[PDB]
Amino acid sequence: MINEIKKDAQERMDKSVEALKNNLSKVRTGGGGTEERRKDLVKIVRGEAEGGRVAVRNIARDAANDLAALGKDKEVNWFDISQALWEIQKLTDVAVKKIDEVLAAKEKELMEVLEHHHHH
Image (cartoon, rainbow, N blue to C red; front, side, top):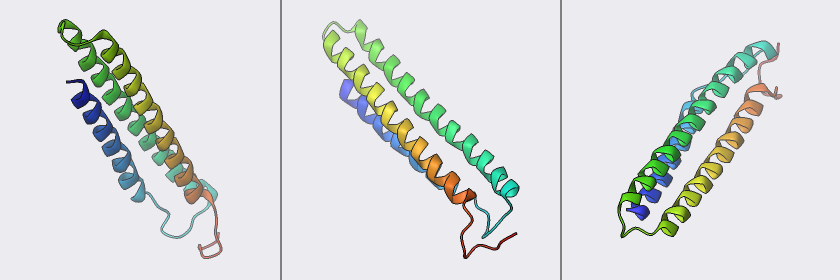
C-alpha cells in the first residue's frame, strides 16, 4: 500500500499546485491600475496561495495517517513506513516551495507597472 499512498499524494499535490495556477490566472488588472487597486488583487492571490498550502498540508497529513495505519500489519516493515513518512515530508516541502514561488511571481506581475500598461 505504501507505494500507492506515496503516488496518490504526489498526484494530489501536483493537482493542488495546478489548480492554484489556474485560479491565479483569473486574478488580473485588465491592463493597468493604481498601486492601491493592484494591492487589492495581491491580497486575493495571497489568500489563494494559503489555500493551496492548506490543501497540500492536508494531503500530506492524510498520507501520514494512512501510512501509520499500516502499522497494524506485521508484514509491513517499520523502516518502510519510516522512509515513506520522510518522503511525504519531502513532497510537502517541494510543493510549498513551488506555491511560494508561484505567489511571488504572481504578486510581481500584479504590482509592477510596465510601459504598455495604462498609467494613473
